[PDB]
Image (cartoon, rainbow over all chains, first blue to last red; front, top):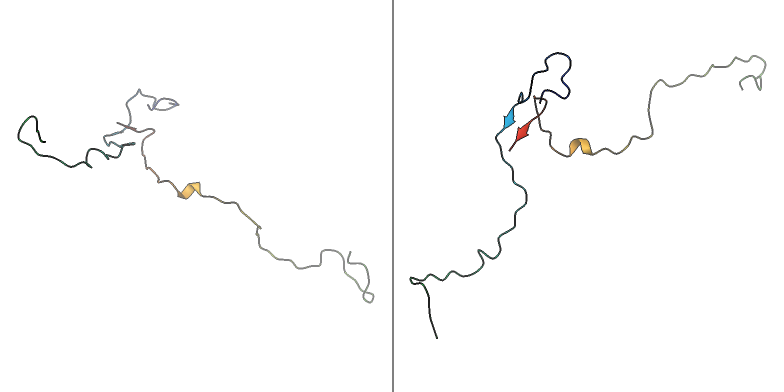
Length: 50
Length: 50
């Protein structure tokens, strides 16, 4: 961390730096089939019609 | 020259001409990368994030 290069004063070891807890986000698919098709509510397990 | 032609007799030596004290140049370049992306300020040698 503070190494590479540590010369000539304080060398110390490694973890000697502030870290950031913030996240970021890359790519995504845009959702085009999960919200485009009509919902049919039903109270059973199978629905039948002629 | 300055010694030719003597008008009519009396003439002066070389380096008798007044000039302009200022500095200038015809062109510079084009420059754009230094004012494009944001700056990220950082006190430490390095920074980590998840």
